[PDB]
Amino acid sequence: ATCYCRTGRCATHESLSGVCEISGRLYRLCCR
Amino acid sequence: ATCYCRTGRCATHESLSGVCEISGRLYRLCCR
Image 1 (cartoon, chains in turn cyan, yellow):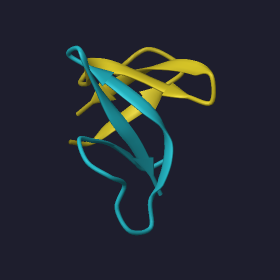
Image 2 (cartoon, chains in turn red, blue):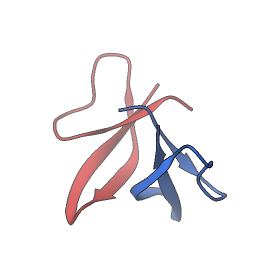
Image 3 (cartoon, helix red, strand yellow):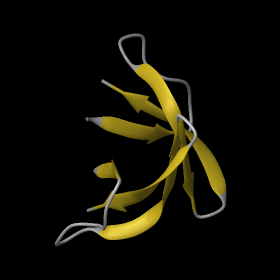
């Protein structure tokens, strides 16, 4: 899958597929 | 960043960078 751990909302044509934990902060996992 | 949420270990050239949670399972976040 092609995904990004985003500080903000998922982009156009992405879906929220889960979350990322990076260095004590939570991120959206946005995938397309 | 170009990262993958992997079921297995990170590749030799990748850097373990965090954790993905997707549909009730945890995955390594492995980044180029």
